[PDB]
Image (cartoon, coloured by chain):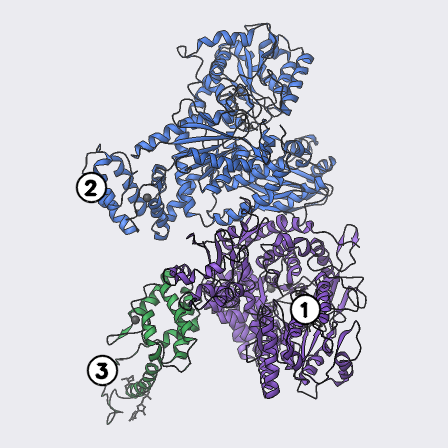
Chain colours: A green, B purple, C blue
Amino acid sequence: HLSAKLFHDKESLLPLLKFLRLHSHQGKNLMLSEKIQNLNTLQHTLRKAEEYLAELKSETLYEEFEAKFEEIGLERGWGDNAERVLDMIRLLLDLLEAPDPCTLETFLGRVPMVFNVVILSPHGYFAQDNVLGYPDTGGQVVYILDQVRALEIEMLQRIKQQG
Amino acid sequence: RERLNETLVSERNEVLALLSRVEAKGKGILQQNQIIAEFEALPEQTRKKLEGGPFFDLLKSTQEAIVLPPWVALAVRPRPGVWEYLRVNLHALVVEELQPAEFLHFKEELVDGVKNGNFTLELDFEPFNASIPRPTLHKYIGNGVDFLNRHLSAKLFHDKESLLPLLKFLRLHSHQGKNLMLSEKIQNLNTLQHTLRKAEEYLAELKSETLYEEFEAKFEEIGLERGWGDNAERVLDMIRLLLDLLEAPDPCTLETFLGRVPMVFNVVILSPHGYFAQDNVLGYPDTGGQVVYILDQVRALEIEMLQRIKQQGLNIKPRILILTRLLPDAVGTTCGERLERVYDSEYCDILRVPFRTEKGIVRKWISRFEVWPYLETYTEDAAVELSKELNGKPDLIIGNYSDGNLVASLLAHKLGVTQCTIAHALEKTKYPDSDIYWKKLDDKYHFSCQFTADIFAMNHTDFIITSTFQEIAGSKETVGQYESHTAFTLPGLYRVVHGIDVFDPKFNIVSPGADMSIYFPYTEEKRRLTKFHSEIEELLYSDVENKEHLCVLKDKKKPILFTMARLDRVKNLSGLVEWYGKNTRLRELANLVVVGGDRRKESKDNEEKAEMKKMYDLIEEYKLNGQFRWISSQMDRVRNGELYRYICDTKGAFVQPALYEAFGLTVVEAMTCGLPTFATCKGGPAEIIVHGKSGFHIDPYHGDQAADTLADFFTKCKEDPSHWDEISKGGLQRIEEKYTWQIYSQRLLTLTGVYGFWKHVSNLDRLEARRYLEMFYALKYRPLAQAVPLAQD
Amino acid sequence: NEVLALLSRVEAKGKGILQQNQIIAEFEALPEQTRKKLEGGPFFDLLKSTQEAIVLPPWVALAVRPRPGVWEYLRVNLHALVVEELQPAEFLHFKEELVDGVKNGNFTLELDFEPFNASIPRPTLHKYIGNGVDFLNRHLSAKLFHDKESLLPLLKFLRLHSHQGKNLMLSEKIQNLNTLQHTLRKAEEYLAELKSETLYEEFEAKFEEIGLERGWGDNAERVLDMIRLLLDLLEAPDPCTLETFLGRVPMVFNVVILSPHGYFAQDNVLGYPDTGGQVVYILDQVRALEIEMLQRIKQQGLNIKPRILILTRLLPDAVGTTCGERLERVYDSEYCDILRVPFRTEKGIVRKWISRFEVWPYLETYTEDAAVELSKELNGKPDLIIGNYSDGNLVASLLAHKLGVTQCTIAHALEKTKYPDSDIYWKKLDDKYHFSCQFTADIFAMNHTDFIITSTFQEIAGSKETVGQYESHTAFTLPGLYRVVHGIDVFDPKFNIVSPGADMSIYFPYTEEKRRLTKFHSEIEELLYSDVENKEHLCVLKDKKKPILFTMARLDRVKNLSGLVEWYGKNTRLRELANLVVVGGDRRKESKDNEEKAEMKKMYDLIEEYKLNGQFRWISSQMDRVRNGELYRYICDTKGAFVQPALYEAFGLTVVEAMTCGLPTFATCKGGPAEIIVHGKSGFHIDPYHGDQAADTLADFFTKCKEDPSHWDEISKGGLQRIEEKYTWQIYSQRLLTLTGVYGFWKHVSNLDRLEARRYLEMFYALKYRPLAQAVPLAQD
Ligand SMILES: O=c1ccn([C@@H]2O[C@H](COP(=O)(O)OP(=O)(O)O)[C@@H](O)[C@H]2O)c(=O)[nH]1
Ligand SMILES: O=c1ccn([C@@H]2O[C@H](COP(=O)(O)OP(=O)(O)O)[C@@H](O)[C@H]2O)c(=O)[nH]1
Ligand SMILES: O=c1ccn([C@@H]2O[C@H](COP(=O)(O)OP(=O)(O)O)[C@@H](O)[C@H]2O)c(=O)[nH]1
Ligand SMILES: OC[C@H]1O[C@](O)(CO)[C@@H](O)[C@@H]1O
Ligand SMILES: OC[C@H]1O[C@](O)(CO)[C@@H](O)[C@@H]1O
Ligand SMILES: OC[C@H]1O[C@](O)(CO)[C@@H](O)[C@@H]1O
Ligand SMILES: [K+]
Ligand SMILES: [K+]
Ligand SMILES: [K+]
């Protein structure tokens, strides 16, 4: 539905640009800066970034091209190296051009977002010991402790891959 | 207008950078593109140039600088497919913004002395394009099907009226009175949604390998005819893909489903000009890579069609016709027989139809530039014959080259059939400034007809196939072949404002190949044909001078510098022979063997004739006897294959010195055998070859540098024979990756489906462009075509 | 009735290979058969509705016209029945074989304009035919309603709008709908508290500040109304509001009118070949138009001075006329001028008058020269361009395109309807009439123009029983040349019927005595009743007291004056009752026109053959309208009548003039006069195809009038009233300027769709017209 609604529609695309521009964590800018006010500059800047990156060695760290990227309006979180930053910029350029569902997901899922997470489990005796089997204490408690551990490994990773 | 700014920089680099603007205006009244607009004042300047700053863009992107009034008309190309043209004054401060149809107006004032008429024709196809939006993104150039898919995938998503066409499409679909896919039972999406639902449960239960014959009974009941699959497993997938499009269309699915619907049964391929034959032809005027491409293409195609028909659960038998001219008088050939079976195919047949006038058929061969008056009556006739040969109507028409695309359009329109074009070359890029200088070239080359027909076909066709990206958008530095038709002018005739857009979703790149049984690595000894080594050794090292071969090779042991091609001005064989003759170091390292032209018979082609006079003269001038062997056309590919490998034994190289080459199958063949290849950087081979890895590039405009580059190569190879083996393996790998026949057919068939379905939805949007084209042909081409003198028997 | 139809279809095939028209396509078949008809049944009415049938030996093709604008084409095997529906193009093949023995080249041109018109949906109702601006308003109204993307064009249109460097409407300070919206109510607040009469000068200060430039009105009352109009349009657009607003915006300042063919002058011309109601219409028109143009410009608080140029051909050797001078002021106008420019070639200026059918080779250069000349004359470029007739519409198109101006066209006649079967038989007629050229330009300008003005509904959709003038261009064919599948549509919103009138200074009732111009009576009595025979008049009237049957018109084939004379000549009874006075041809000179010459010889022989002396007075062309007004009134004094025996008449200005004067009128039923007159009420209709019947009818009018004198007055007053309603110049001028506003704007909104049409038309002009036109032989001095 989003892939189809996004295909060559201005009033549609803005939301995605507003998103990346507003995106920040703990007082740091991510993705696009305030330098990019419209799809034209964004389109132009991405293309501009792509020409540059397609030149560099794949394993080149973001810190190298950081200065330049800051110039043209690109904040951190596209990836930790040239290769990664490249696929990502190429991904968004594509959403602007010919959106497909697989692209759309891949990009949105890649954008660093989830950092802080709040999980709700009020009832029961919720603990890591001396509990399981008490009234209301059971599969929910187990699931949640496994979930967070699994969740934390994935986040540290996504965070590190996005530089 | 970014390129009118960095040039505004005459405020900084001025007293230097207005010099190059001098040494140009100092040549005068002409066009110099690139190498001349560049190898001019910049290289021929002094170190007070020092223009290596921000200026080096606008000159590096020009493509032309046309000397002019106290004015310079120039062009600039920021990115493939994006246009800026400049006009500035030398000493007058005349620099002016230039917006298209205005810039052309300045090209006309540079010939006629004034621009074209007033109400003289402007050709703009842009407004007829508005149906789909254009990709602005480089990746989609030559990828259009991928773009059209996503446009359809979206347009299809939860739109009632929008899915109807797909139902109607699958509902009407039939072949020779057999109904396929959906029967007439299913009148609406709800019934189809449901009927498909019912079908799925049933099939999910059956074993994967259950034949369609079992459940055929059930299906006919619910409205499902044949063409879904041969067994249950297949029918299942297919049914699932259709359910999917009805719910959440995604591009990948839409393509796959349209890909599989059994569609292409009878193919009709247009190739009127030349001597089209499978033996005793190649090397003749107008007879060349296009004939090889088509013969290889059809064989490949026939196979894919067979296994697509089998998989889809159908026994229908395909037929592929190759339409071409019947030349009753070409003797020593089969060109005089109406029907001929293609080698190694069950269903591919050559179908020959004669040209004719009200005075009866025309027997004599005719140059490809002169066939124009004949083509419309050819179409009518061909229609009649292929109606005879074909069972039902054509499911695809492929046009080839210029005359071929002209006709295939008329048929496609007449019969209402999906159409594809393949240019195989576009003369405007091959014969420079033939657009603007057209009027003087006309009585020889008749370019007013050819261009007209090329423009007509590009826009008439459903999709276009190119063999490379370069054939469309060129490169960063240089303009592409099709691209160069976006805006041009034929002063006194008409002015093409927007003729084509490289971003058009109809461009698809499908790269051909070299037949693998004919051309393979010289290293596989089991495969080598030694039966030929006597003929070949006579061919090369024989003592005799005759119509088959000229001069002689004193030293039998040198590496051979080899080339083979039709003989005409553009192939530039006379060029290479000269470069070699002037460079003593190359002559010592290698023998030069050029195969081209047929000297066994008197030549009837103007260029062929002119080329021979130059060859003849050079041989004497450069005293080539003993280092040079000029061999006549080799019409048998099997032995040609072994010839290439033989050249490998001598550890030679292959050189292709064309002023322009559209694709260069010889390049592909040479590498497929493993022969390290040096080829012209102008046109297709720029893309085929990767410099210093899979081969080397040379510039036909600097020949002396080419001859030396080669001398270098042989020198290194003498010091380090492993250097040869490295380039050899590089070529072998490049071919194995990019150029092969296996995927070609699949791509091509898939395309026919996607574009076939598409042309139903877009039916109404195109209706205007259709009348615009009808008129262009009738009121533009026809008058021009009847203008051309008829051949006289 | 399976055994029945086979019969009529048999009787049809009996006449063999041919086509026949709807009169015959029935009037022979149905009636000429035995009582075997017994068909009042539903099959019948395919026949009754058939406009023509084309019969080729196995086949009969049918063109059916159920309602104006609605066509069905069928084929029928003359034996075996088997009715099969055919597409227009295929019905056209039928005609083509009928002439060439074969259809047009498989690859020969089909003109189809339908796919280019689709921007607006088409009205299907009879009422919107001729009423297109009404339709287009409702469309723009809806389109505009709470759509920002749709409202922007309105803001930009107004923001860019200017004349000759003076900004108008909105300044550049208004960049968007909020600012416009906010500013407009700011202004409205302010004006509400001013006295209505406050002049725009007082608050002009404020406005400039907030982005409001001049042209909203003269006083505060009027700037307020317009502003409120715009507020509404941004808020809740309705059709009426939209139209009032657009018709109000000052636009038309300079107007250019194209009328190249003929001798265009204010005196010493009328009745000369190719010179007639078009010169009359245009002159009346520019007058009325300048009046309104001035009030509008004044009412909007603008001080600009308008200009109207009538572009026509400079004829150096026309003598006794003003056709040799380059600029001529129009009588009773401060701002209207005739601007003459010569035809010319590589050899230089062409001196001799050339027939309308021959001007084609010259028209493109004319355009360029015309352009250069009106650039010197006009202050700023043209705000409106009106093409007239074919040469006129053609040039109007090219100039409009060249200059980027809103174009209107007026046909004044369409030859295809004047010269039956001149489309299908075009080849044998071409050497003489060059219809391949004309039809081509007719089609070109018809489509290329921004809108169209007709003088009747008949001009578009004709009547219920018969085909209209533009209607007959919907689908037709020129064998061996090209085929028009859909060339025009009677429902195209571009059509507007704006009826013209007669100058009411010149034409009034014969019963207003103080007004009659008596000083002309000596001249008229000599003109009519004198015993002298010369190049001014032939024969003589023996009995002075009889009533006069009066006609006046250009002299040529179609006007059918030679017919009228023969009718009269054959009919003794009419001859006893009334004297026939015909005015046509200028015999003072040698006739340079083919038809005029031919018609003259016919006249002479009719005189001798029917012994017309004593009942018949043949007067040369009366070139002065003022005395003409009184001449009409004189006929009334005698209780006579005006008759107009044309085979076809596009509009009939003389028919309007006669009526305006009180003179009972009998006019042809073929073309415009069929709408103008109401049989038995405002006048009568006669059939030029049945002449003797026409005469008998006239005899009858006079007899009735003889016995009862008040019958003459019923009709006299009947027409007087009719003209008072449908035909006057008062609303014309205002309607026209309104359309220029609506269509002026609509062309900004629709501009992107007219692009495809632009290129189509360009290529049609270039690749089809030009080559045809050049083929026309040039004149020689
Ligand atoms: O005495 C107990 C009772 C339960 N469990 C654990 O609690 C979970 C029970 O979850 P389940 O989803 O099976 O049932 P639920 O408690 O969610 O209703 C399982 O991991 C058990 O191993 C346990 O460890 N000790
Ligand atoms: O004497 C000759 C000359 C030409 N060729 C063949 O002609 C084709 C030429 O194709 P290419 O694209 O290289 O040049 P083209 O003629 O198509 O412009 C190649 O397959 C060659 O092997 C040949 O077999 N013998
Ligand atoms: O000898 C003549 C004949 C014509 N008229 C005028 O020319 C016009 C004829 O216009 P109409 O539309 O009736 O005929 P048209 O010439 O346009 O076909 C009328 O105003 C007549 O009064 C005239 O003044 N003298
Ligand atoms: O309903 C099952 C119960 O067990 C839990 O999993 C807790 O361990 C909760 O979901 C709920 O209290
Ligand atoms: O223009 C090059 C020529 O060579 C061919 O390959 C011959 O088969 C054709 O493409 C064309 O006629
Ligand atoms: O055929 C009709 C003729 O009548 C006129 O109105 C006379 O001026 C012109 O439009 C045309 O020449
Ligand atoms: K951000
Ligand atoms: K079917
Ligand atoms: K303004």
Q: Position of residue C398 (x, y in %)?
A: 51, 40
Q: Callout 2, which amino acid? A: Tyr
Ligand 2: image quarter: bottom right
- Give the residue at mark 1: B574
User: Are the residues under badges 2 and 3 in a single subunit?
Assistant: no
Q: Horizontally, is C620 left or right of B83 in the view?
A: right
- Give the residue at mark 2: C190
Q: What is the spatial separation of the Cα atoms under label 2 and label 1, in whole angstroms?
A: 87 Å
Residue at mark 2: C-beta within 8 A of ligand 9: no
Foreground residue, A62 or C65? A62
- The label on residue B315 is none
Whether residue A84 is situated above or below residue B445 in the rendered picture: below
Q: Is residue C472 visible?
A: yes
- Give the residue at mark 3: A122
For label 2, the crowd category at 10 Å Cα-Cα, with few meaning under 14, some 14 to 19 and many 20 or more, is few
Q: Quadrant of residue C595?
A: top right
Q: Position of residue C35 (x, y in %)?
A: 69, 31
Which element type, helix, strand or loop, lies under badge 3? Answer: loop
Q: Residue at x 53, y 9 (%)?
A: C707
Q: Position of residue B701 (x, y in %)?
A: 59, 68
Foreground residue, B609 or B733? B609
Disc 3 chain ID: A
Q: Position of residue B624 (x, y in %)?
A: 71, 75
Whether residue B711 is situated above or below residue B777 in the rendered picture: below
Which element type, helix, strand or loop, lies under badge 2? Answer: helix
Disc 1 chain ID: B
Whether residue C612 is situated above or below residue A140 in the rendered picture: above
Which element type, helix, strand or loop, lies under badge 1? Answer: helix
Foreground residue, B97 or C628? B97
Of marks 2 and 1, the one in the foreground: 1
Q: Callout 1, which amino acid? A: Ser
Which quarter of the figure is the C terminus of chain A placed in?
bottom left
